[PDB]
Amino acid sequence: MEYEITNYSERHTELPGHFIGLNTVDKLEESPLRDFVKSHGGHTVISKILIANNGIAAVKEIRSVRKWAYETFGDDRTVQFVAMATPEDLEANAEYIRMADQYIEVPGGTNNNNYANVDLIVDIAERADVDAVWAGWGHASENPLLPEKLSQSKRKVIFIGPPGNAMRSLGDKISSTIVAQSAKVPCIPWSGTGVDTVHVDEKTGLVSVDDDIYQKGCCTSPEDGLQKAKRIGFPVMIKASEGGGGKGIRQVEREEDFIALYHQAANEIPGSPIFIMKLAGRARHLEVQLLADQYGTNISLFGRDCSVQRRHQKIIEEAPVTIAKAETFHEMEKAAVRLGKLVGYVSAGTVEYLYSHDDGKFYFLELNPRLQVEHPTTEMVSGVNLPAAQLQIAMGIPMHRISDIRTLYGMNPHSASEIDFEFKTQDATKKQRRPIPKGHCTACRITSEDPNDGFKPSGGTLHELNFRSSSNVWGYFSVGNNGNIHSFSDSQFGHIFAFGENRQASRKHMVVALKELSIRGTVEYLIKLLETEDFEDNTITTGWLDDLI
Ligand SMILES: CO[C@H]1CCCC[C@@H](c2ccccc2)OC(=O)[C@@H](C)[C@@]2(O)O[C@H]([C@@H](C)[C@H](O)[C@H]2OC)[C@@H](C)/C=C/[C@H]1OC
């Protein structure tokens, strides 16, 4: 078969070498896959992928890509998958291992010994002679050394995700906020407000902040920090930029406690720079789904509202966002895009925001440089197969030649016409359709207890739920093997996704599914949360669930 043609050869010359793989279209024999990549403007044929993950992540990657492969080439194995298999996963007969076209055994224990071990991943990538590695979420997905070492290999292995430079462009909290401010993204009042000068390596695009600028947002002494705190207004947070987890951080309610608490945080992470920031109160946590190709094009795929949290853990999330005014969320989308373009982002990513419904303002929190477990919420309302889009982007195919994206913008999916994603001109508004979310999706995190008792557990590590009473709901529970904290566990986590024509409908469908599920040997509190007046009226906040407890 033939396709409409895109010639991006000039643009290919500008791309950093780490984007280019070994099997480039120019020196490759004709084939369905090669023809597709070439005609669509891509540079490298990715026909074999190593999955540096397990559980639901590995299963989702395989199913999403194989579905795209089948729809596109009539052969769902056009792009092969190699799996990494720990003794724990092998012993549990994990589905992803059985699904993969091939697999390689790896050491057990915590993930630093396997799925998150960069050197091992690179070694296996070479041994398996793969074209690319997909990490997804968790494990080493956010480790810049992964794409860097993969590209340094003589096998020139591609990373299906953002480049190391993009991940590094957003360093500690201080450097990260300054970069955001340089991209004109509103940030929470802090000791560095106004500091927005960044340095971009004219050759690598790596974004950094010179020491003389970085220090502009740091405290020179406890007394200096107090002065900065007074200006910002109490309560504030004292934070050591090099702080780990919950160390090097202290909330200050009153001036009188500042100095003492400053030393407490400083002493936990000695020598670390310290910055002051206003304390976020009960508000909203919104996310913008970012998708970027290798040619500077960053777009948003609407967003998600994950305000309902417990101990900072997302429990209930929905897409698209509805609490914010349409134009205000569009501003969050645009700011996310500005940031993505600045750090040279590529692939899927999320920009998190703090949003106050009382005054309608929003503030940057962070950019998670990875695809998230709850991504199907966004996939459902946008119609975009995200793992397939990531794969095409990794092959060098531009945003406008990704079929699901063309469909989202109301274009003929077979056409090669350029798309103006910013709708800047009358011509663009004439040939394109502004994306509109299709329906609504509610996602709930669910937990289960399946103690390891010697008895052979139900085969597989991904237990799927096929609801008999609901038509718009799907869910799963997964055995947590080889985590960073637990190599195996009695507890099992998962998610349930429910679709509806609108917020009320998806909510209703979720409740119906949960009730059906509750007829099994957990989700009882979820049903109550979903049927509360506050949730129904959408008057919840980031502190809502914690206040109920
Ligand atoms: C682990 O694999 C599960 C994942 C299900 C995720 C929930 C489900 C859904 C969302 C909301 C409500 C109900 C169900 O989302 C979907 O089915 C949609 C969005 C989606 O993920 O389907 C997958 C792809 C075509 C693509 O990525 C995307 O389509 C654009 C296919 C491969 C389905 C795989 C499933 O296995 C059969």
Image (cartoon, rainbow, N blue to C red):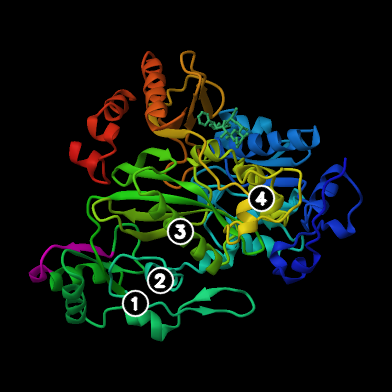
- Label whose residue precedes the other's in the sequence (2 or 4): 2
The label nearer to you, 2 versus 3, is: 2
Q: Amino acid at mark 3?
A: Leu
Tell me, for residue 431, which label it has, or none. 4
The alpha-carbon separation of the residues under discs 2 and 4 comes to 34 Å
Residue 266 locus on image (x, y percent): 25, 71
- Label whose residue precedes the other's in the sequence (4 or 1): 1
Determine which residue is flagged by label 2.
181
Secondary structure beneath label 1: loop
The alpha-carbon separation of the residues under discs 4 and 1 comes to 40 Å
The label nearer to you, 4 versus 3, is: 4
Quarter that holds the C terminus: top left
- Displayed quadrant of residue 209: bottom left
Residue 28 appears in the figure: yes
Q: Which residues are magenta?
A: 248-257
Determine which residue is flagged by label 3.
367
Q: Amino acid at mark 4?
A: Lys
Quarter that holds the N terminus: top right
Secondary structure beneath label 2: helix
The alpha-carbon separation of the residues under discs 3 and 1 comes to 20 Å
Q: Amino acid at mark 1?
A: Gly
Determine which residue is flagged by label 1.
194
- Label whose residue precedes the other's in the sequence (4 or 3): 3
Q: Residue at x 39, y 39 (%)?
A: 317
Is the residue 254 above or below the residue 203 in the image?
above
Q: Residue at x 63, y 51 (%)?
A: 430
Left or right: 349 with respect to 230? right
